[PDB]
Length: 153
Image 1 (spheres, rainbow, N blue to C red):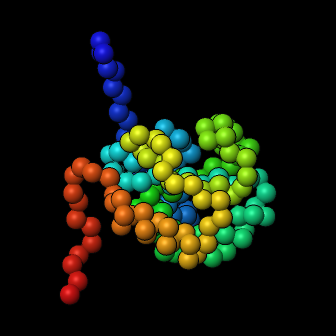
Image 2: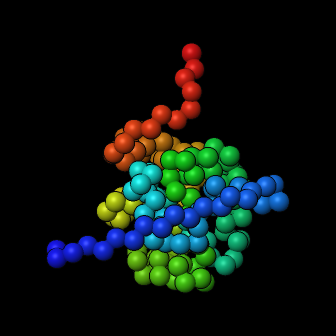
């Protein structure tokens, strides 16, 4: 390793209001960042692919995603990142794991980038069980500790 070029760039929005949806959940339309953040934030990376046809998604988006808990978790615990196949990001992602069916949900590591788990069909009960089990079994990334939320009881 002769030399290592570094280029950090900060990105955020000052102006905000109801007129606009809760971007906090919807991550940027970038792949690099998704994995990147995982490091700094030290959180898991959750990928979500949805074919142009929302016929299959509409099903999950009903209770699966609709679940405020699932969104709050996938946004907090993991990094909410979804992209259509038609788009470029989606096209590539396919070759990555040689995707073919849909929907397609999996948990990748923002540190190593190696598929740890793979699930074809998710559910309100299943999704949670699996996720929760992984969070408690493995645990959030390692690094700096940050106290979130006050103490009760």
